[PDB]
Length: 48
Length: 48
Image 1 (spheres, rainbow over the protein chains, first blue to last red):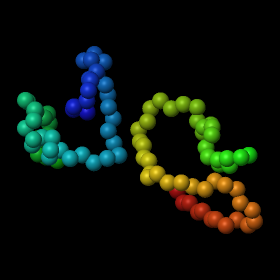
Image 2 (image 1 turned 135 degrees about the vertical axis):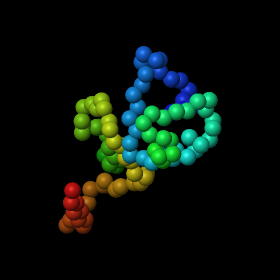
Image 3 (image 1 turned 90 degrees about the vertical axis):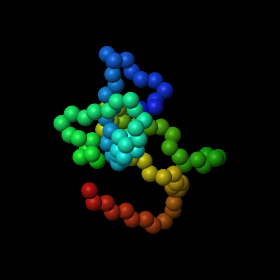
Image 4 (image 1 turned 120 degrees about the vertical axis):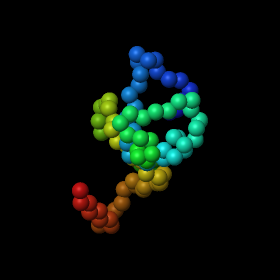
């Protein structure tokens, strides 16, 4: 999803529902592969 | 006739589907749909 070939327009933003699987956020938040990252309401560490 | 086949030909289970919130698929296999003569050699009981 983060590296997909194309993304939808800002007005036509796609709404993707994710379920029936597991999420490994360690490789995402802690990889420092993105310029900026922030969370609202809950810290990234607690979300894991 | 010849080339007994015995495989799915037409799909009449449902006409169309628009929104899907869950999906699951098992591993490939082959089930013998060929007809048999005699008594019932198989029994399946399900609880849902």
